[PDB]
Amino acid sequence: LFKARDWWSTILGDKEEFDQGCLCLANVDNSGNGQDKIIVGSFMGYLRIFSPHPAKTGDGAQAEDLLLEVDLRDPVLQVEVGKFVSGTEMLHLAVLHSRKLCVYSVSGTLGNQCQMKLMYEHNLQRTACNMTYGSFGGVKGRDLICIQSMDGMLMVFEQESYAFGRFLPGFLLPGPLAYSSRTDSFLTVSSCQQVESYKYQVLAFATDADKLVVDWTLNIGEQALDICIVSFSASSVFVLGERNFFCLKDNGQIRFMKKLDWSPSCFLPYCSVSEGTINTLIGNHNNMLHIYQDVTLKWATQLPHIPVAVRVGCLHDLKGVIVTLSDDGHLQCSYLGTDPSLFQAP
């Protein structure tokens, strides 16, 4: 419908591959102006951090958009940013690899325009799938990390130290994973198409699953692509299925659901523009990017490439900037649709 109001794009490396998990938007250098940076890891082992600026010429020398590029020499499965270091609330970068989790401190402005120093790393006893993080147990001021292994163990790390590991029951292939702070629970979706919620303390105290009962379960009748837990005060569990999009109450009841008319590739519940409603971005395999308010389509744009991940954040000193990443490394920043009361063509 609308073309993208893009203002920056790049191509990451040479025939590199990416998936959901590889894109993070966060104030990873703890800057005072509160701007996000784009962090992207690739399956080719490169970690890149950008602070994009629109084209600006005739003013001599502009600082590079690329703040940092490092070859981690190990495929990157996921990147996240959070309070991963004990004794400080500063944000740090977690990089998930198949057999290790590495946590880094990224400096402000100092080739590379900042430094990235390893704070600690955990060597994993099992191959990793994906991870989530948060204030497990209701601890304030720190983000613990939970990694799901390929064979279905949830491995919990209390920042610099390993806490425990528990095998999921009813497990076949690893599904998406998310932490709900409101219910202090881990959410996933199993191969037999059950959304499952596990209480953190039940996990912690189920000492007999390291070789565990679900809190609630919901059969959604299809495979899940992603889960996103958001609150913009009443918490919601969003599930992106292959055929449907779901919004669940914390207790596992469906709040609403919507049949999708196109195969989705990725999504992001990203804001609320009115009380009781939520806006969700959904990218698809036909290069379209959609915005729904609850289940109602509000806006649509064609992208040049199929997004495997989409994020919204603060870039170029503007809020609500859309960042998309394709599976072959096309990275693009764009602005949302324009106010229709401000312009209409004759």
Image: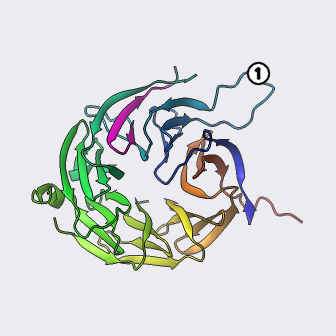
Tell which of 181 and 215 is nearer to you.
215
Point out the image quarter for the N terminus. Answer: bottom right
Report the magenta residues as a range. Answer: 92-108
Is residue 280 positioned above or below 7 on the image?
A: below
For numbered disc 1, what is the local secondary structure?
A: loop
Vertical comparison of 326 with 252: above or below: above
In the picture as drawn, the residue positioned furthest to the right comes out as 346
Is 9 placed above or below 291 here? above
Residue 107 colored in magenta in the image: yes
Horizontal side, residue 278 vs residue 99: left or right: right
Image height check: is 247 above or below 159?
below
The quarter of the rendered structure image containing the C terminus is bottom right
Q: Quadrant of residue 122?
A: top left
Q: Quadrant of residue 120?
A: top left
Q: Bin the neighbour count of mark 1 within 10 Å (Cα to Cα): few under 14, some 14-19, many 20 and up.
A: few
**Does the magenta run of residues contain 55?**
no
Q: In this figure, which residue is indicated by the disc labeled 1?
A: 60
Q: Decide if residue 77 is on the left or right side of residue 120.
A: right
Left or right of 303 in this view: 319: left
**Main SS type for the magenta part?**
strand
